[PDB]
Image (cartoon, coloured by chain):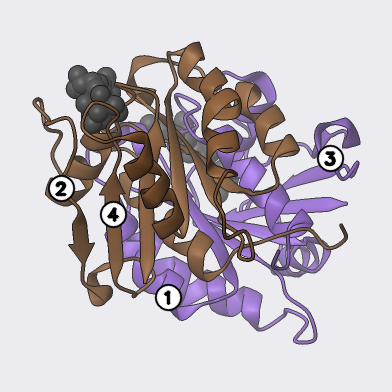
Chain colours: A purple, B brown
Amino acid sequence: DVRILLVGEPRVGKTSLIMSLVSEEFPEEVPPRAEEITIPADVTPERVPTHIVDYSEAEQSDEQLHQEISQANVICIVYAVNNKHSIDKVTSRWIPLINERTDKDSRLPLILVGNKSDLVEYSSMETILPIMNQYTEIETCVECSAKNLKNISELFYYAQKAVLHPTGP
Amino acid sequence: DVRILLVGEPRVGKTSLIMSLVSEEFPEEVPPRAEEITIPADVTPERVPTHIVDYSEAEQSDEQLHQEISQANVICIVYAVNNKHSIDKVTSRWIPLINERTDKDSRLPLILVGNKSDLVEYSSMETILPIMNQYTEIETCVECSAKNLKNISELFYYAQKAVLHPTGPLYC
Ligand SMILES: Nc1nc2c(ncn2[C@@H]2O[C@H](COP(=O)(O)OP(=O)(O)OP(=O)(O)O)[C@@H](O)[C@H]2O)c(=O)[nH]1
Ligand SMILES: Nc1nc2c(ncn2[C@@H]2O[C@H](COP(=O)(O)OP(=O)(O)OP(=O)(O)O)[C@@H](O)[C@H]2O)c(=O)[nH]1
Ligand SMILES: [Mg+2]
Ligand SMILES: [Mg+2]
């Protein structure tokens, strides 16, 4: 199975991203944590289902976060393109937290997700490129907007492919 | 060296994409074909020297297109999200033509680029997902907007990564 987990600082748009995918429409309001979302195996050529899991610090303990990290086989670290603090925390908090707990005999791909592209005129790539170069665990990066749905489809396609295309050609 | 070639139907935005990458501003006027671009290693996403080549049917012959395909080590097939014809030509023209190359001993990764995302509120993913499924030589896909400077840095990062770190399934 593909088991996707979204982590990242509060209010970067994790839940909104998941619920925008669900309804193909931006929800004006969201709960702290979305329900688990299922993509049936019919979608991928590998005939494998996808599960999408949300994390909310307001609702969940660090013990629960660690277990979610253990269950996931691809982790989207979400930041907001208009929030430097959320980007800083990718390297000061999220990557070390995940890496400390990953199986060193294996690989857990990470995807850097820059949400709220609808708010800004310029790219976050210049800022996140040095993070990419440092951590080969990061499989790819994407900028998107839950508000207008742009690149949301790509986001979860990339996450699936990080698991289903995990080696070379 | 990463050697990128942009192909695709007329007016999908190949030249505008390249010039928006260079200038970080959308050119309201573009020539038919950008001049060949050579970018130093330490200013590119993957830290390797990068060449970017533009194709223009009015400016170049079929022989020159054939030469450019053999020289590239990643090809971005550009379509316009609001032009179904430019999408149909991805499979009817561009992929077969690329597979006419003579030296097939090395994989030539492809990237599907849906430009002009500023014009529409829907994704082209449903349309191009069947293409991705049928043609495993396609490494990834991206939707961008030269006009709004969206996902242009991503596009060229994806292109470099296809050369240096191509991907594939666990089992064939
Ligand atoms: N403009 C804009 N606003 C967004 C976008 N995505 C989410 N928001 C807004 O950002 C705020 C936070 O969104 P959430 O989905 O609750 O973010 P979260 O990461 O789940 O927050 P926590 O659960 O507290 O960690 C809400 O007001 C959303 O409406 C976006 O893409 N663009
Ligand atoms: N709205 C919008 N228009 C674009 C975008 N990119 C290019 N255009 C416009 O599309 C037209 C064609 O752009 P070109 O860059 O000349 O496209 P091309 O693929 O190089 O065309 P040929 O060289 O003739 O094959 C021009 O009017 C551009 O201004 C875009 O991202 N959004
Ligand atoms: Mg939430
Ligand atoms: Mg041109």
The answer to whether any part of residue A28 appears in the image is no
Amino acid type assigned to the residue bearing label 2 in the image: Glu
Q: Ligand 1: does it lie within 8 Å of the C-beta at label 3?
A: no
Q: Which residue carries the number 3 mark?
A: A45
Protein chain holding label 1: A
Protein chain holding label 3: A
Query: Compared with residue B62, is residue A3 higher up or lower down, i.e. above or below?
Result: below
Residue that appears at 15% across and 47% down: B35
Q: Callout 4: helix, strand or loop? A: strand
Q: Callout 1: helix, strand or loop? A: helix
Assign ligand 2 to one image quadrant: top left
Residue A35 lies in quadrant: top right
Residue that appears at 57% across and 43% down: B100
Q: Which residue carries the number 1 mark?
A: A133
Q: Earlier in the sequence, mark 2 or mark 4?
A: 2
Task: Indicate the quadrant containing the N terminus of chain B: top left, top right, bottom left or bottom right.
Answer: bottom left
Q: Which residue carries the number 4 mark?
A: B52
CA neighbours of label 2 inside 10 A, class few (<14), some (14 to 19), many (20+)? some
Residue farthest to the left?
B29
